[PDB]
Image 1 (tube, each protein chain N blue to C red):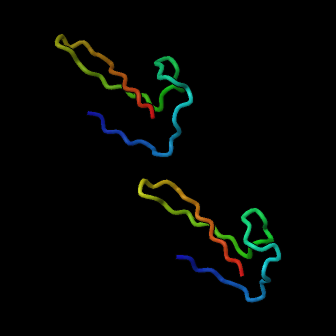
Image 2 (image 1 turned 30 degrees about the vertical axis):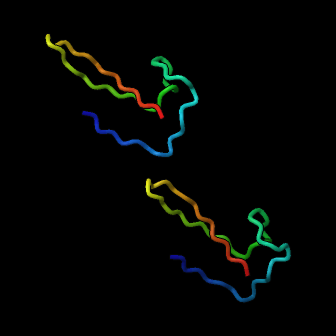
Length: 50
Length: 50
C-alpha cells in the first residue's frame, strides 16, 4: 500500500513521454522495497505523472 | 466578509467605464484570497468605483 498526497496545481510535465532516465519526464518518484520467495529485495520504483 | 472605508470626496472616474488596467478608472482596488473545493488559491480583485 502507498498512501500519497498530490498537489493539484502542479503542471503537466513538458518532457513527453515518460522516461526513467529523464527526471523532468515524471512528476514524482517513490521507492518501496518488496521481497520475493527467496527473500531477495526488489526496489519497486513507482513514477507518478500527470 | 469585506469591511472597507469609502470616502465621499472621491470623484467619478473620467474614463468610463471601469478599466482594470487604468488606475484612474477605479476608485479602490482590494484583493481577497479564497480557496475552492481542492484548496487552490484564487485572488478575487474587488473594485469599488463611485
